[PDB]
Length: 185
Image (cartoon, rainbow, N blue to C red; front, side, top):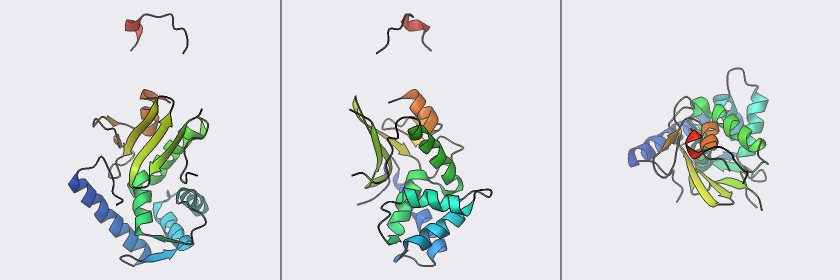
């Protein structure tokens, strides 16, 4: 039963209400399904930046909405997509942010799973990125109602972060250090 996590009841319904609104504005249909290309195209137009080429937005979205092979999409697909990188006002910023990190660290991020690092979003709690590192599994939640301008990441303790970059700074994925413990900030 797909639902966003690390979210209060109210936040869940608020977010659910948003998904409904956007799906409807994109498909003029309360539910059902639509051809894959049609959804991605409408979503691109509506989610890209003013100076962002439509084709670019289409390629990005198409890559995130795996599998490529599937021919149609539904509300639950939009729910998943907005859960990972919403709100829509800054969706492309969150994407670039996260995407840039993995591109610089061995490309661990995958939107369609099938030693070393690996990360993906939980299909049943779509705003939750699961990370498989040496020290084990770690979880971090995108807050789908917070624009990339705010603190849109929160952990299991309720500790917010400013951005993906900040979070992976504070908790990245030994070497002889010749400096006293208290020298550390």
